[PDB]
Every structure is written in structure tokens, then in C-alpha cells.
Length: 116
Image (tube, rainbow, N blue to C red; front, side):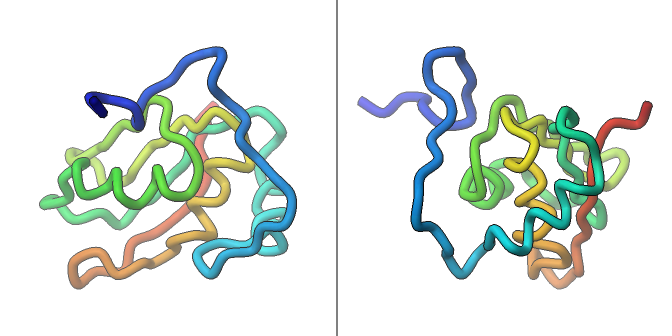
């Protein structure tokens, strides 16, 4: 009875942090520097350099791993992944978690959101 748990969003089911945590994927020290970029508000992530053949389905098993996906939105007609995580640092982790990661023979990209 799994149905649809991940890739969701709510109110009484957020903030799942904890002490002692420094995995190989992403680290804290390599995140605080990113958070400084944008203000403590913008959550929309950014992962440019995406191949036209980039199915969101294959993107789930990558972003959701970093933090929590509320309403991830793919942009095939542009070239960039927009993830409005629940927390600021959350999405920011995706910028220091991949940054030119091996997807399918192409060096992806990273960045922040909020155009205005």
C-alpha cells in the first residue's frame, strides 16, 4: 500500500532534519556558501543544462533524494529544472549535490530561482 507518498506536499508532514549528518552525496559545509547567494525565502531550485530526453520520472530518483519535493516542475522547452522545495537550504542542496552531474553524456548545471 504505497500508492503515492513522495513527490507530494502537505502541512503536518515537513521538517525532517536531524543531528550528525554528513553523507558523500552532499555536505553542510558545502551548502552554507550557497544559501548566502539568495535570501532566506526563495526555494525554487535550478538545474540548467538538461537534455531534451530528460524524463521527470528519472529526475525524481535524484532530487527527492536531496531533500523533499513539493511540486517539482520540469522544463523540456527551456533547459532547466525548477524545484520549489519546502525549505530554502533544501533546494540549495541540489545546487551542491549535482552541479554538472553525469545524467546521459552531458554536464548538467545548477543555480538559484526567483526571477524577480
